Image (tube, rainbow over all chains, first blue to last red; front, side, top):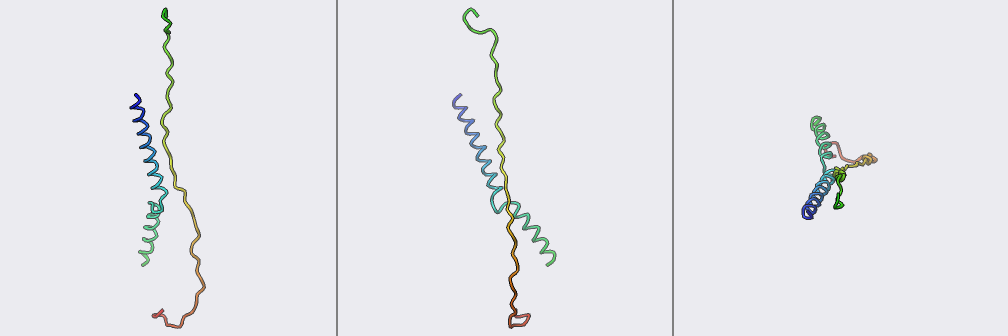
Length: 49
Length: 48
């Protein structure tokens, strides 16, 4: 039983680390929002060019 | 009972569910680049 409780604590640690990775993907500067803005602005400039 | 063990069984309270962790990406908004003062050079248009 104590081994299974330690296993559940391991799974909670895995959930917290996956949340930390998701927060890093949100909070990085080179996220999807920067690339979305880049492709929209560059599509406009590309068409006028 | 005769031995002191209870007839009626105990209540089993429900444990709390594991919550779902939330994150967010707050964003900033700095000003744009403003145009400096223009100086006239000495060369013609294709050179400049």
